[PDB]
Length: 127
Image (cartoon, rainbow, N blue to C red; front, side, top):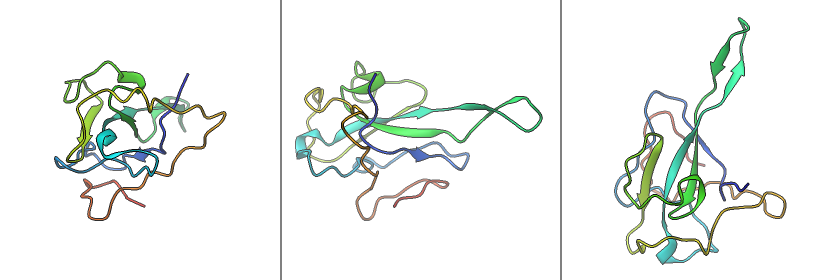
């Protein structure tokens, strides 16, 4: 009943999303150095195509702070298909339930922006 705080990263290539061991956490001025840790979750959608058959759209990757979201129970590093982990140096490996997720009724999504020098895999674009 709740959404990611940020807009999604859309996967346009065959590469899966992945970041080096200090990159990938979206910028949020209303968060602290301890909170800068979370995961991206892949969300695939299916639509009626041109032949009338079902077809997959491009996968979307949504960021959630650690301890929040559809995989709030997973500890950092947990093995699960469709889940990739990110953290910045100094972040605390504790659940961020104090941040939680977004209610689109009273909060717009934060435009996802990565800090200067973030290395993305092929098929991903940083605004």
